[PDB]
Image 1: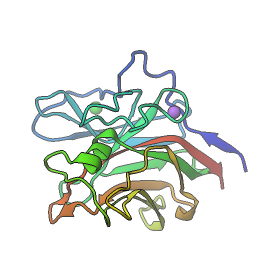
Image 2: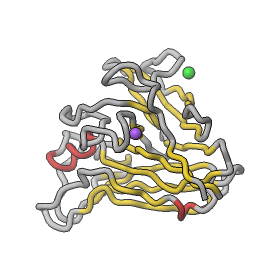
Image 3: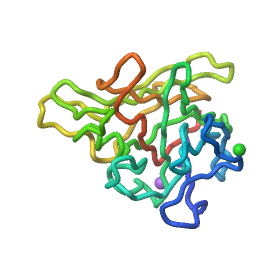
Image 4: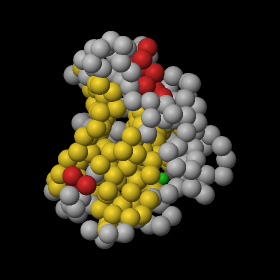
Length: 222
Ligand SMILES: [Cl-]
Ligand code: NA
């Protein structure tokens, strides 16, 4: 069964750049658009706005941003992509005003094999020292990403999970590397939703940044 790695290389011309929607960002609400990879394998949804501090995204975004020092950076804590220079930034929430990151496989001969995943700098900084809204992690805290698969009609096909932090003691740290997230348990999913969660949460949702990163998204033939 042939494997293909989705790539957004050769799309960004400048350093420290990201996908920018065709529409006009506003400070009222997120607007939604989509982008597909150059091989027309997967459609990724993308939310965008500008609340007054510059372009703000949710859902998926391809970028080459390397800043792993600024407290609110969407860049992986590694400060670099797993493969090449381009990776995918994800800001995903579920619920009422939720902006979930849901990809759709377009070349339906393929299913997802998996992906590399890493913590965003924003989520990592929140866990190691807090960020006002988020509090520093201690024994018992965790950070998770759950992938839910669906068929074309939207019927659930399977679910997979991975931890990006799991503090057994006050002295532990979140995952600082790219790690492999096996997505074959989603079965023949066409649509895949990625939702982050944290032990640092309340009634309104999670306090740790709902930002994480993906790279080397791999498809395998069914
Ligand atoms: Cl648009
Ligand atoms: Na990459």
